[PDB]
Structure formats: structure tokens, C-alpha cells
Length: 187
Length: 187
Image 1 (cartoon, rainbow over the protein chains, first blue to last red):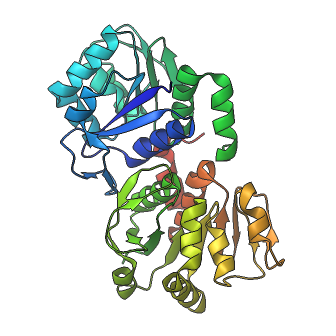
Image 2: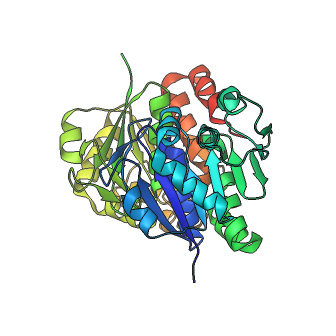
């Protein structure tokens, strides 16, 4: 039985931070659903790459629960995730069932908006730190990937492979992560 | 006047190797056209990410010439590039006008198919070396990015940022590449 990942894709998402995790998680044999926040229609990402989601978020939620919920970054995509009641509900449910939540770059600021994971050690993009830390609800880290139990965060486009492989390791183990890593030609 | 990049997107392309260069080159202020080999329709990449191109290749060629032509990898995407007479013509024209050609992972094997850049030092993904080297028409390198004048090659998903920044440096200079690099949180 394979594990399953939900990647929530909003307008203005960082496309690298969306595609690198989708691709690497699929390389691990984990089922990934790319779910469009707004509906089934194509999504215009932050640098104008247009990605067609697999399903609407409304429909994807009906097929869960998922072993991980992944939030890409991009400032505007993270704000759209932060403003969504649908996202609030999915994250609350995932937290309540003790499932993994992973967010990168500005993505962790949607955890703040939805009051998810307070008391965890987290990282973000440097430029998103102040937003994430408003109120002191998390403990900040400069690690390129941070994991404090079921809240897994990372910093930017250039940490996306590390982020994705950390997700793979958390769900499928260190050996699978190592096997997936080698053909990527990481340094 | 900004420089311009053509990224040719075929079915089976490696989506990370497509999106990372598009995004990073756009961050450099270079105009990028994502051109669909088959037409204007969405493209199903190697790990099932679906990307909507900006234009068909037929239409994009009408708006050139471009300061760089970029060939993503992915075995099946590279084979589709290798089989295309339209791609042959674009690459031949680009070579004839002394314009940069950049290819990553399996992408350089389309240079072999179209007889482009023989005598250059090149790299590829390790698993694409034998195909690239059939006939000894290139000199192989294990550098993560190789550039021998106007032929710029790289190895895999994990070298895509380095590849893209090398393209940026070749077109816009080292200072712009450094400015674009810092916010990415590369190691």
C-alpha cells in the first residue's frame, strides 16, 4: 500500500517549490495529488509557469486522508493558502490525526495563519521570518530543513530537493530517500 | 533591451529541468518563451506534472531569434526533441548565428541527433553518457556544468540551478547571476 501526498497549489505559488517536491515524491513511489486551491483550472505560478492541477482541492479532500500535506511557498501563493478556510480545515484535520505537514519558503506562514503547530521549531525563507515569528508562536531555526515531529519546514527554492527528500525519508525511510537521491546528481 | 530565451518543452520532459531554468532565467529579467514542441496544448512531463506552454514552437520560432535555446532533459522528452525536424532547424540556425545553446541531463543527446556542436566538451547525466558519446563526436566532462564556448551542458535535476545560473551569467554577466542566486538559498 503506497503512501499519499497532497500538494496544494495556489495562484502565485513558487513553481520550483511545487514541482521539485511533486517530482521527487513521485520518484519515491508515493502517490501525489496536485490540488488546485481555486478549482480544477490551470494555475499561474509566481514566475508565470502555468501548471494544470490533478484535481480541485474540493475533490482531493474527498479522497484523503493523506500521509503528508505539502504547502509550497511563493509570497502570493502562501497568502492565498493563508486566506483559505478550506486549507484551514485540511490542516486542522491533518494535525488532529497526527499526520505530517510540510511547508517551504513562505509556505510556513500559512501554518501561522491557521494556528497550526504552535510551539514547534520552524524555518522559513529569511524574508518570511518576521511574518512567521509575529507573536513568538514558533521557535526559529536557520537549518536548511527543520523537522520538529510532524511539522517539517524548509527555506527556499535552493532547499527544495532537501525538503522533498526529508518528506520521502519521513514517510518511506532513509534507504528509499538515499536511492531516490543518487540519480538526481545533487552535490 | 532584454535578452530572450527559448525553452523547448516536449512530452516526457523532466519537469524540474524545465521549471528551474524558466524561473531562474525570468528572475534575471530575461524574457522566456516556453514553447511546446507539439503545439499549444498542455504538456505531460516525465513525473506527470502538466505544464501549459506559452506558445507553440511553430509560433515561437516566428518571434526569434533568441539569445539562448534551452533543451531540458528527461529521456523521453530528449528523444522527442531528437526526432523533431523543427528542433533540428532551430538549433542549426542558432549555431549558424553564433547563439548560445544550453542542454541538461539527457537534453544534450538532441545535440548529437541534430549534429550540433561537434568537437565541444560536454557533460550529460551519467546514464546518458554512452548515447551522447556514440561516435566520439564530443569530449566528455564530469563537471556539473560544462561550457565550451556556445555549447553549455549540465548533468541532472540537482544541477539545474547551477545550469540556469550559468545561462544567466553567459547572457547578463556574473553580477546579475550572483544577485539572482542569493535569494534562492542555495548551499
